[PDB]
Amino acid sequence: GSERIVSLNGDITEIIFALGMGEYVVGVDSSATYPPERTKMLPNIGYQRRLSAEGILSLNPTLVIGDEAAGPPETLAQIRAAGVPLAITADPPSLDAPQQKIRFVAQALGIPQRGERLAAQVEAEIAAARDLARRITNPPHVLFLYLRGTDVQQVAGRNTAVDVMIAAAGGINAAADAGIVEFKPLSPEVVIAAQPDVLLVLDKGLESVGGVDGLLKIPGLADTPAGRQRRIIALDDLYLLGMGPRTGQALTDLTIAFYDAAQ
Ligand SMILES: [Mg+2]
Ligand SMILES: [Mg+2]
């Protein structure tokens, strides 16, 4: 019997491939960039937060699977009303999200023992990266910026995935430390007070502002130690924010970079 999975979030998609079940995926979202060579060859269903039932359903799924980032809620009710099985998992901002999503997905795909194996492997890489973070004796102050050209310019504080990543890697989230919760508009006051040692951004956000030169035209950013030293870390969003099987690898990368910033 044929199995036709539609996955609604990139991290969920990454888990499906990592569990060795990628051949059954018929549709993915825009954020599904890993493994790049395999996902870019698959039909897109749109933006994970801006979904239509028509988009999902006309791929003729046997199963629709995602996490709490998938929406809107009303589209999700349309899937269930069509009688297509729908499995939505929680995705909390914590280092426990990867293992929880892995087990949920493996169970939803009837391969729970495979999910225990991958979850353990991922756990091990997370633990190994956190140990590498013990190299840092002087935690750098890090500011995460969420950028979309001039339309969106935001900082991330507490109760986010990126906050967890910054801390686990041995950095201080400078925005969080100043009391910012979730995503808030970036102000010159916040940046200047924070004096971040390093600016953390997304690949596509950094391109969208016109590279490093564009980024440093945002008011307040140039007058920070990060701005003066051009100390910018850019990661793709799925890798940094997704909390998927590669979390331990992103942490290793971040902590290596945070150590350089600490020097
Ligand atoms: Mg401060
Ligand atoms: Mg997610």
Image: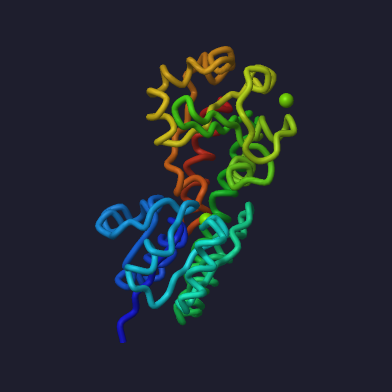
Relative vertical location of residue 173 with respect to residue 193 in this rendering, above or below: below
On the rendered structure, is 3 left or right of 86? Answer: left
In this rendering, would 174 be left or right of 24? right
Q: Is residue 21 visible?
A: yes
Quadrant for the N terminus, please. bottom left
Is 194 placed above or below 145 here?
Answer: above
What colour scheme was applied to this rendering of the protein? rainbow
Q: Residue at x 68, y 18 (%)?
A: 189
Nearest to the observer: residue 157 or residue 29: 29
Q: Nearer the viewer, residue 12 or 167?
A: 12
Q: Quadrant of ligand 1?
A: top right
Q: Quadrant of the C terminus?
A: top right
Q: Identify the residue shown where x is 29% and y is 59%.
A: 43
Q: Quadrant of residue 177?
A: top right
Q: Is residue 26 left or right of residue 202?
A: left
Above or below, comparing residue 21 to residue 219 in the picture: below
Residue 255: x and y in percent read 54, 40
Count of number-bearing discs: 0
Query: Residue placed at 52% from the left, 47% from the top?
Result: 241
Q: Is residue 195 above or below residue 184?
A: above
Q: Residue furthest bottom?
A: 1
Residue 239 appears at what percent x and percent y?
45, 48
Percent coordinates x, y for residue 132 in the rendering: 56, 45
**Residue 8 location in percent, x, y?**
44, 61
Q: Is residue 123 visible?
A: no
